[PDB]
Image (tube, coloured by chain):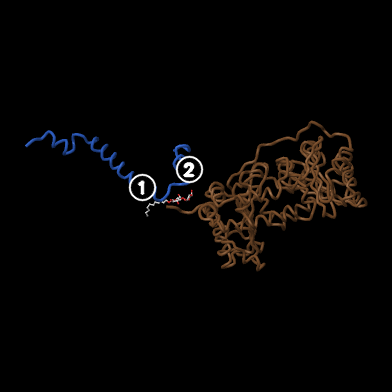
Chain colours: A blue, B brown
Amino acid sequence: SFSSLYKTFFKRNAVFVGTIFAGAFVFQTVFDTAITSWYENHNKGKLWKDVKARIAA
Amino acid sequence: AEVTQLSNGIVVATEHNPSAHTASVGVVFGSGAANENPYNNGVSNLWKNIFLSKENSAVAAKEGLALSSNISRDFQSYIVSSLPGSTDKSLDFLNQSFIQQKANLLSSSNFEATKKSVLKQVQDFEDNDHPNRVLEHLHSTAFQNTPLSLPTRGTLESLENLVVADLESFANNHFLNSNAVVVGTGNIKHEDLVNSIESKNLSLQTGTKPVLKKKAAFLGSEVRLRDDTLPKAWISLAVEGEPVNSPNYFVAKLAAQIFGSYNAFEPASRLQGIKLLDNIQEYQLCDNFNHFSLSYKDSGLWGFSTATRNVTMIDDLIHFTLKQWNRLTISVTDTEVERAKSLLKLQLGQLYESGNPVNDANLLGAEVLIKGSKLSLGEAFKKIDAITVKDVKAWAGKRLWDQDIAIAGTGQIEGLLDYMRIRSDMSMMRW
Ligand SMILES: CCCCCCCCCCCO[C@@H]1O[C@H](CO)[C@@H](O[C@H]2O[C@H](CO)[C@@H](O)[C@H](O)[C@H]2O)[C@H](O)[C@H]1O
């Protein structure tokens, strides 16, 4: 949070109810992106996907 | 015919009226109760009150003179009023008082009879003149720790701590020529005064400038003087306004004009074409109000002032009003603006065109100090009218909407709400 980098977009008013919901909509994909990645990695080798890999039938 | 302005060392200004029965002369020092300091406060109102002590005022009473005096914030004046023919009878009595005499008014029997009356003076004011009292503190908190803060008539504190050695400490610094202007108002010519002025010699402390301080500033704040023994409730509120000689000087005076000034008693007032009035009147939320755009050299105060015997419902009072103020940014009717432009003019008139010379003095003296000259009514009007709605919607858009305020008050103000409410009503929720 820096007074320049904020005031650029929003001058001297808060966020606006709809811009919020917009961010919310975006954040919600961007997040479930990151976190589901970091977690699938942290558990590398362990996932059935990684085990489906080696194992053959 | 267009106001005269010529300087030979002493900047001599005059303004003629051919239908005036009398006239007036005097000086205006371009330094007022905001050139003082924390502990010398009221020095400028102390100077005014010796100047009218029976001594000097009995002198000019045989002569047929009457003296006028006032102190403001940015400025300070000393005026004398008489018949237009006794125009030398003025100039000489002025000359005596401000270069000739010094300790004739500065007696230890004079000064301890003036200071023992500017003490009773500032002890009926803060005691029983709440509307100005409230109005005065409003400056104290909005402009806290800065020039404008000091009450013009000075604190009873720094007013019992001051001797004659202090009247002078301010005199010999700020009572100069390069900070003053001589005025001629009413029924006299420019070639009557500036002649009778270059007739007299001498020069007091030539080359000397008066001194300076940290330029004033503004900060959102409150100060509350609750008093549940006082039958009403007095409140004054405002934002960082606009200075004298600011691009929006008139834009801002037009805004004030819109909501204006109420008196719940005069049936005339009840009918004004003011939107806010629709609300306030339902339950009789107050006894009166009025707005303003006080302009000073460095900073200003746009807001309003109200008294009310209605204690349980003050919270709406402040609410309806500050919401109206939002419209000025988002939804002001053009046809409201015209009624403004219109009414501004009528008010700005009785201000400038009153048949009383003493006013035309301070007006002249102050303005011809700060910008050099005066501005004509036709000049003012030519500006007032240029003003669109967009004028008012961009001025409120910076000055009014979501900006820090400055409340002050006394009486039954338990009902007057808090700062995160009040301040928050500067805006409205948007999608
Ligand atoms: C129970 C489930 C709840 C779900 C989540 C709720 C999310 C709420 C989001 C609401 C955002 O609502 C938003 O509030 C801000 C104040 O911060 C408002 O801002 C308003 O007041 C601010 C001052 O605070 C002013 O700067 C501004 O000019 C004005 O529009 C704005 O009109 C609105 O757009």
The outermost residue toward the right is B62
Q: Nearer the viewer, residue B159 or B221?
A: B221
**Total label count?**
2
Q: Is residue B238 left or right of residue B377?
A: left
As shown in the figure, which amino acid type bears the numbered disc 1?
Ala
* Image disc number at residue B45: none
Check the residue under mark 1 and report the chain it is in. A
Compared with B279, B100 (above or below) is above
Compared with B2, B322 (above or below) is below
Occupied quadrant, residue A45: top left
The outermost residue toward the front is B1
Q: Nearer the viewer, residue B86 or B114?
A: B86
Quick one: label 2, few (<14), some, or many (20+) residues within 10 Å? few
Quick one: label 1, few (<14), some, or many (20+) residues within 10 Å? few
Kindly identify which residue carries mark 2: A11
Q: Is residue B265 left or right of residue B160?
A: left
Kindly identify which residue carries mark 1: A22
Picture coordinates of residue B172 (x, y %)? Answer: 80, 36
Q: Is residue B366 left or right of residue A7?
A: right
Q: Are discs 2 and 1 less than 8 Å apart at CB?
A: no
As shown in the figure, which amino acid type bears the numbered disc 2?
Lys
Q: Is residue B255 visible?
A: yes
Which element carries disc 1, helix, strand or loop?
helix
Picture coordinates of residue B140 (x, y %)? Answer: 65, 47
| Residue at x-position 33% and y-position 44% | A26
Q: Is residue B312 left or right of residue B119?
A: left
Which element carries disc 2, helix, strand or loop?
loop
Picture coordinates of residue B53 (x, y %)? Answer: 86, 50
